Amino acid sequence: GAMAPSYRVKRMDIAKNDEECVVNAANPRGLPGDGVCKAVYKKWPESFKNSATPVGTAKTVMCGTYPVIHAVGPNFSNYTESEGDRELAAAYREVAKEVTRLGVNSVAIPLLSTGVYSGGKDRLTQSLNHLFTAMDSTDADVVIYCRDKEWEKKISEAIQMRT
Ligand SMILES: [Cl-]
Ligand SMILES: [Cl-]
Ligand SMILES: [Cl-]
Image (cartoon, rainbow, N blue to C red; front, side, top):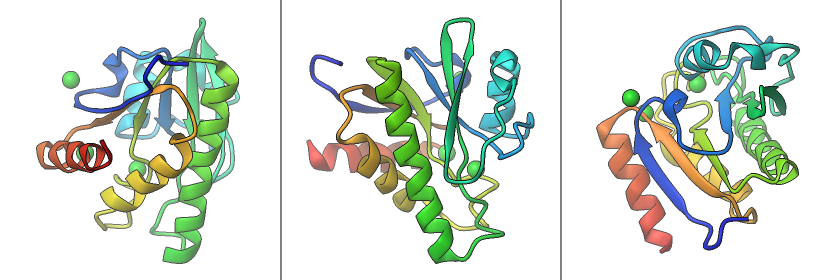
């Protein structure tokens, strides 16, 4: 575990993270996809061997010795708000299990279902709170990666609120 487990946020490409493992915002079919998923595919293409997994689950594939945790959030274009919320919560609980099993002291994580899977809605608070519910009982240093300057401020404020 980390000596004093923390949350941090950085506004940069998760493919250039400084953590002991990465969470991919994956699609269920293990396809190269777009956004975070395409950057992850470019950086760790070996990690996409048998990475396909259902919505609401996470599957880890090693790139050399570096673990890539493929976490499949719901596409809110297809799910009801209620079912989508349940699957989004589940994907993050499966991430917490994998981070614990791997014995890492740190993990880089994007906000699941906040991009092309958002169904056109702002889900920063919804996705971040599900992230907190899952990861609060783990002792890894969590580093959240985002690309928008306003999101970086909003994520930083939500972290500091609990401190
Ligand atoms: Cl960058
Ligand atoms: Cl997304
Ligand atoms: Cl963002």
